[PDB]
Amino acid sequence: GPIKVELPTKETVEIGIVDYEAGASHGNPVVDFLKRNGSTLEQKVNLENPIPIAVLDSYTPSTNEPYARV
Amino acid sequence: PVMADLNGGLQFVPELKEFTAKLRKELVETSEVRKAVSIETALEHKVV
Image (cartoon, rainbow over the protein chains, first blue to last red):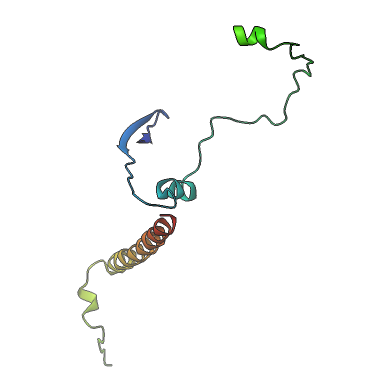
């Protein structure tokens, strides 16, 4: 996969590749290295507190043939 | 009065402080790089 450098505009551009290829192994040393030395970029960011939206009742139908058909 | 120079020609080395700070960095950098590269090569071998 690509290695990208952050530019001054915070855009990222490709400056090289990761290219690891092993036979018999107990692990991925690339990811082990990046976990220990780098930080994980998480796209998902938790709110301070979860905001309840709804607690909703629903029913499963008496028969599964209608869903089976569509 | 006698003035004895027992300085081993040290005075003829221009910009001595910078010269000593460069020799120190060239040595400490080589030490710390070799430590880090050997620790990571051991951890890679351990994982594989």
